Image: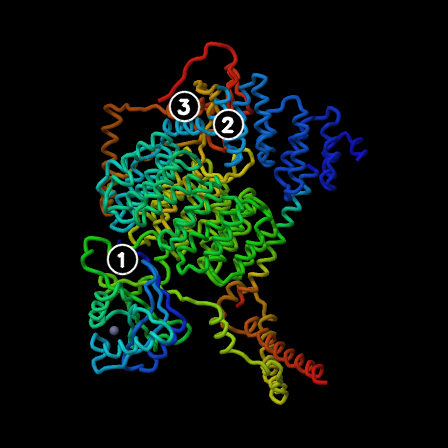
Amino acid sequence: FQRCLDDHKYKQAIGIALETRRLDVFEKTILESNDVPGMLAYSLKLCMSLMQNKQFRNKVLRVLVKIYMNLEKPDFINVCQCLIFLDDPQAVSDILEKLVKEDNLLMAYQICFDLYESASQQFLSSVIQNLRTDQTLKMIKILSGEMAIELHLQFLIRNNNTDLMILKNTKDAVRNSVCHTATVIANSFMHCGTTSDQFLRDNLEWLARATNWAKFTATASLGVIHKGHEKEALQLMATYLPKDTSPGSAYQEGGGLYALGLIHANHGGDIIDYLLNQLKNASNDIVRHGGSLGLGLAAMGTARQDVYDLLKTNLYQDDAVTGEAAGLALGLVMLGSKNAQAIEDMVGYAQETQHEKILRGLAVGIALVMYGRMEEADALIESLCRDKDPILRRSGMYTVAMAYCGSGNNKAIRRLLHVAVSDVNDDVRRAAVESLGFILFRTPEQCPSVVSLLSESYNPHVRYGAAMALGICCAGTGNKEAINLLEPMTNDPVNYVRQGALIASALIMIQQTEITCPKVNQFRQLYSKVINDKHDDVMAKFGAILAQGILDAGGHNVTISLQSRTGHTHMPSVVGVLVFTQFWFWFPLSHFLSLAYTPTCVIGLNKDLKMPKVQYKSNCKPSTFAYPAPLEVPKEKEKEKVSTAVLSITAKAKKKEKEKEKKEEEKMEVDEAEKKEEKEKKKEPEPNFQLLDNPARVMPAQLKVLTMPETCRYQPFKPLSIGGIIILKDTSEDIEELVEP
Amino acid sequence: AVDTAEQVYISSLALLKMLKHGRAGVPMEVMGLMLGEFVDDYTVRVIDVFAMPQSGTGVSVEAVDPVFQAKMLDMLKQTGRPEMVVGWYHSHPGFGCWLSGVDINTQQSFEALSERAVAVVVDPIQSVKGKVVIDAFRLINANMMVLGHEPRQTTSNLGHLNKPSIQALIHGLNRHYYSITINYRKNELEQKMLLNLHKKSWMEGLTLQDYSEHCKHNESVVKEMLELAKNYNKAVEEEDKMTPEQLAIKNVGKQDPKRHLEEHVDVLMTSNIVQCLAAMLDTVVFK
Amino acid sequence: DLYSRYKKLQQELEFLEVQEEYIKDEQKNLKK
Ligand SMILES: [Zn+2]
């Protein structure tokens, strides 16, 4: 190592220093002489990307924050890149109280936004308890995440690019089947978070045609449109109460309660208490669904005891139909908890009951009670796989997915795929090969190489979960190798594996134009083909209409990503996607994918209210992309002719007629002309410097090619190469131009 | 408040009573009852099946004997378990499965008395090889003529288990009755006792079949394997550019070069090793 | 680069040992 000191190159030194687990040698190579003090930026990504163990990982991560505190400026990156992994609540609260104490409310204002976007529930609830132990009330709201929601609501109400006619050209092709549910899940997706009501307004008699569970689904879709609508939604569905809609319709009032849960997800308030008091005073059966699904969704990740107690005595009712309702919600309130009583009561209750709906609700629930434990589940992981209950073996496969999310464990991928080949039920073979993407989504290079040969199996159940493994591993990238695999998958003989190929195709290419990847316009007309064909299966075209809703979700402004901004992983985008895969067993679980709709936006709010109108531009390399025009080109074709092929004596007859024009045309008068190259002229001087205001949609590809106006004086604070929210460093004087609709 | 994509659980003990009693009276369309429990809205289970004495009429409402009914139910109350009847079945030998015009009237009688009263149709003489032509059905109303018959809902397990077959939709499918799915209440301690007791051999595992026919069979394969090797000589020394990817495909015959080859080498290997290895063990074990 | 190449060779090596494992396992289970 002294030779590595005599190297003067110290990345050679830092290799051995992390091999032999010694850490004072680690500290000295960064507190060396002045040779690039951003070696910590190399070492952070080195510990971020390729560290398998977690036992000494936090130790190396917290010997980093010793030199970050000993660095000149503490605030910027070290908290939300290290301490949220190291989950120290009061360490964050104290040093941010330090940052307020020197009267520095500009960068503490930044780090609270970055903390709320990245870090999870109950870490923010724990730090905000140690907050209150004004500008303090300013940092209450931006750590409780209040005003981040309304600006996110402000972005989507300003920007809305949906073609109304696309859903009209699918609506008229719907026969008297139960594709009405497939349409109302489509417009809810592509008006999610928009608060736009026109399809629940104009064709309202058509909406009243489908019944008895579409009424449950359609009024659940109403909560999807009003996602993040905190106070205005409670007075909105103060029209459709659980005692004012209809004394004969419980599906109306049941899905209303589930719609309140879809609005206020990850938001504690009176609505938890309001939904708790209506599970006290409840009707017979199908008020207890959307009550419990809504209540477990609003109390997700809270580990709240009082709601957890009554969901048990809801579960021990042994009612057949609320068993799916209770078991899903019982896991959501204990998500990532690792409780003694929760696993034991739910795996205890999973045998003496005599239905299997009750098993399927508790299937996902006991998989979701543990989340990212990474070694701490293996006694339960082994015990669920050994049992002779096929649903409980299937649930153990979801559990090993959710405990090992984003880790390249060889022990996972060995054990998870050994049962994929060997096991005798086919449903457990799916959830084996559906768990592939949950553990490998962080490195999407491997998932085409490992699922491609399983996509050509002999049974369709392996080929089904092969297709949705591509949909979840490569989440929203332009991978095009997964698209290369899905091309014969959507042309399968079996119907439901065609369905899964359509939905996985819709997941991979959201917000991607033709120049981004060429297979976009191939698949949009392919969706159009199998939705306008009359002799295809309803189940085969169910995925097609749902692929319409995914592909333009939120008016080309939201996206899905299990991966977050700052290297951290989402808890809602993982829970939102896997309970969405339980749409075979229950269609109204399809609303849960709206939890994973993360926005594509940059907002330059510098003060608490001040969002200045700042025009800044991108520098896309030869041309433009991004968020195209709607297509209104139905047809107007004409048969109009059959060409006269008379090659008889006409041939010499027309020739002597052309001689008759050689006396008439060139000897009396002829002059007519037109000008060339006017239409070629305007194309080449084009931009690639497109200025943008700051409600600004931005692709996650073009985050790196956008540039602040250096000719403008107002510069941002954070390095502006990644989308989300930043603050402006407002320099001079005379600030104006605030805008709110 | 309407039907879904339901589920029918039949016990393992039921199914053997079904297709033995059907195979017994193969010409004459046997008849029996179906005894289980309506467990919830949209699953149903049946645990037990007993037959019926056959009348001159055949499968109809008159073959249901009410005095044989209550007496058979009575002597199952005190022994085993009492439960409610959940349907009925009959055997259709000459064709797979569909409710006839007399089948549809006796379904009306039971669905008026009971909740749904699932019928079962079993073809014994078609169910032979490794699959069983058994199907279950349920009569649909005509009051929903302006609404969706088969009122199914929020699930994706309707396109499985059968597409509606052409020989069954030519009859009252799908405007008089609907199909319903069948899977089996299959458990351990009945699975293993039927596995291990039907196919087992203990002392046979180290017998000899000794050598007068074993070493004779070692002549029985080698001889044509010699001639088939000479046929293997023929194609390999041929090796002409007759567009050899076309020359290989225009003479597929389940024949010489690899198909009628080492398949024999496998059988010569497996027979002689298992013979000689069991021979060396008996010298080891017995003194 | 000299350390980052070394870990990327390990991660791929761990991966394509797993893929040769189950294909050898699947081909056994496919013969039945
Ligand atoms: Zn009959």
The yes-or-no answer for disc 1 within 8 Å of ligand 1 is no
Say if residue A118 shows up in the picture: no
* Residue at 24%, 50% in the rendered image: A176
Q: Nearer the viewer, mark 1 or mark 2?
A: 2
The residue that label 3 is drawn on is: A681
The residue that label 2 is drawn on is: A113
Q: Chain of mark 2?
A: A
Calculate the distance from the C-alpha at mark 1 to the C-alpha at mark 3: 63 Å
Say if residue B151 shows up in the picture: yes
Calculate the distance from the C-alpha at mark 3 to the C-alpha at mark 2: 47 Å
The residue that label 1 is drawn on is: B150
**Going from the N terminus, do you reach mark 3 or mark 2 first?**
2
Which secondary structure, mark 1? loop
In the displayed structure, would residue B9 be above or below residue A702? below
Q: Chain of mark 3?
A: A
Q: Residues within 10 Å of mark 2 (few under 14, many from 20)?
A: many
Q: Amino acid at mark 3?
A: Lys
Left-right relation of A608 to B150: right
Nearer to me, A71 or B241: A71
Picture quarter with the N terminus of chain A: top right
Q: Amino acid at mark 1?
A: Glu
